[PDB]
Length: 41
Image (cartoon, rainbow, N blue to C red; front, side, top):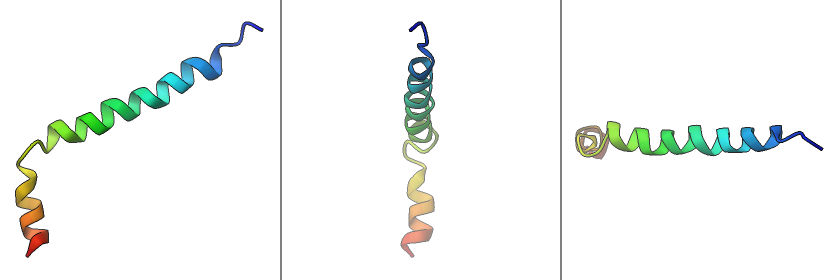
C-alpha cells in the first residue's frame, strides 16, 4: 500500500492551520486593542 496521500494531506491541513492561527496572531499581535476597543464600546 504505497498511498501516503491521506498522510501528506493531513500534514497540509495541520500546516495551513498552523501558519494561519499563528499568522492572524502576527497580524494582530497588539494593535487588536483598537478593534476590541471599538467593539468594547
